[PDB]
Image: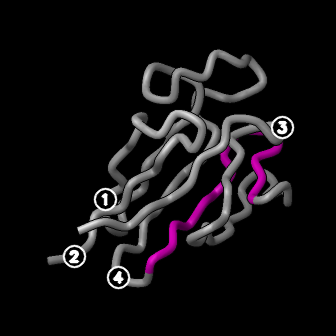
Amino acid sequence: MMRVCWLVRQDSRHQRIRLPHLEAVVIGRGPETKITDKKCSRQQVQLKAECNKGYVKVKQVGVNPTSIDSVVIGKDQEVKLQPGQVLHMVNELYPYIVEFEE
């Protein structure tokens, strides 16, 4: 009954990752994202989906800047990613959005 949370690579929208409700998902450089940029950590962001409330808590784990609509989060800081917002994995590159689907 609860909506599914998808982290979608905005510029390659067939790359989708399931984000389980209230469970931490750590992603970055690797086979899931296909990011090869060495400035992106293998563990760049920690994601906690809120499937009822319709946001995803984003904690920057990597040193280099993760941003939401160009606004930098900062290492160990946490910001809520919302419908319409774009998450850039590192240095305003590699855009991701979140979608909530039945």
Percent coordinates x, y for residue 37 in the rendering: 71, 19
Residue 52, label in figure: 4
Residue 81, label in figure: none
* Residue beneath disc 3: 91
Which residue shows up at 67% across the image and 56% down it? 86
Q: Which residues are magenta?
A: 54-68
Judging from the image, what secondary structure is the residue with disc 3 in? loop
Q: Amino acid at mark 3?
A: Asn
Q: Nearer the viewer, residue 93 or 56?
A: 93
Q: Quadrant of residue 23?
A: bottom left
Crowd around label 3: few <14 · some 14–19 · many ≥20 (10 Å): some
Of pointers 3 and 4, the one earlier in the residue sequence? 4
Q: Rounded to the nearest whole Å, what is the CA distance between mark 1 and mark 3?
A: 26 Å
Which residue shows up at 60% across the image and 60% down it? 58
Horizontal side, residue 66 vs residue 58: left or right: right
Q: Are marks 2 and 4 in contact (CB under 8 Å)?
A: yes
Looking at the rendered image, the disc whose residue lies closer to the viewer, 1 or 4, is: 4
Residue 20, label in figure: 1
Crowd around label 2: few <14 · some 14–19 · many ≥20 (10 Å): few
Q: Rounded to the nearest whole Å, what is the CA distance between mark 2 and mark 4?
A: 7 Å
